[PDB]
Image 1 (cartoon, protein in one colour):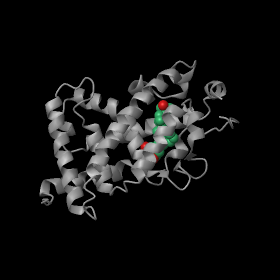
Image 2: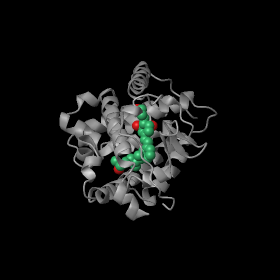
Image 3: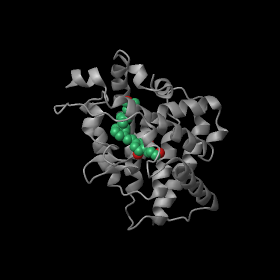
Image 4: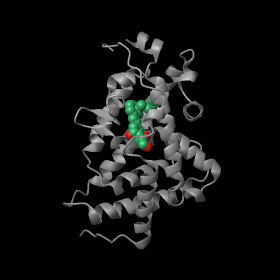
Length: 255
Ligand SMILES: C[C@H](CCCC(C)(C)O)[C@H]1CC[C@@H]2C(/C=C/C3=C[C@@H](O)[C@H](CCCO)[C@H](O)C3)=CCC[C@@]21C
């Protein structure tokens, strides 16, 4: 063929709602960042696990940034068509297991290939590999995280595809501990069908009909980064007085 059905009225509403949800929960001016505990950058040119763990100089700032981001994700998820139809128990399972992956996805909007930084930013609010090691993380997370960001940037997603990919990430029927996997799968399928149809209808050439499979592959990549973050957060958590440098929400979500 191959067939290019038009977006239904419902799929059109779904996309409008997700776009609106993202515009209300993602500030592209980063104007709240001055409210976070300030960034501190110690002398660590090369760049010492002992010193990084001793000082955790960027952790209060980046933990506030991540906590703030988790709050925005909860807000976004609440607006996903169908999410509120789930049990409060399943909503929380989905939120806590996807939070770090959605933060990695939504952070792509501040990421720039100009210098491979998340520029929120300023100079104070520009985050590089070395800022992330100053928060207690190691290259086994950071280097594939940068690779992931570049790979995602190069998909050149429409904002519609970006918000759908975040929604699909969150409403995933295979997360540990979900009860109503069938309901979650139904909601995800509706979103996935919307995304597939959108790409067919609206995405030039085509056939860049590998775009959907490239997007699904990013979801698998995110599971990997999630396991590695979990390992590294555990070792950060062993640092005496680390909990003062985090926040209640971060402690709960990642504990
Ligand atoms: C693995 C890290 C998170 C976990 C850190 C922790 C200390 C909790 O383990 C990194 C993931 C990316 C993260 C990062 C920027 C993330 C952003 C996400 C968005 O929510 C922000 C939107 C703000 C408006 O709503 C903005 O795009 C920046 C920079 C430098 C590495 C990290 C701190």
